[PDB]
Amino acid sequence: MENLNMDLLYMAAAVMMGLAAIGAAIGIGILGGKFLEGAARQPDLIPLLRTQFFIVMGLVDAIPMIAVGLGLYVMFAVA
Image 1 (tube, rainbow, N blue to C red):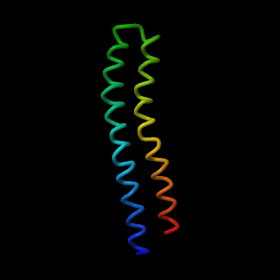
Image 2: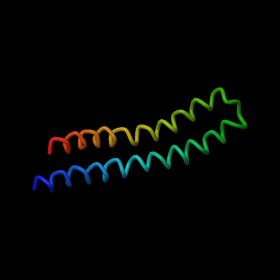
Image 3: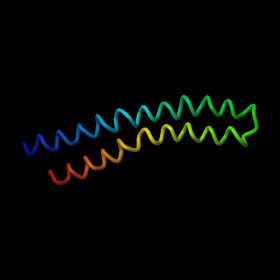
């Protein structure tokens, strides 16, 4: 109950920032890897900046899961 509560809040964060933060990780990797291989043959002036949008597309993916996993981790510390 008290134990189950810490179990609930633990596995909640692992379903949360497990799921998205890895989806983030691969997309920064996939998209931002390929998108800079667009920037390379071009100058790295303009399409280096669009390549930001893509690694950032990844960073935002993990953000609400790491902040909710933070809220779940602080709630674990109470429980």
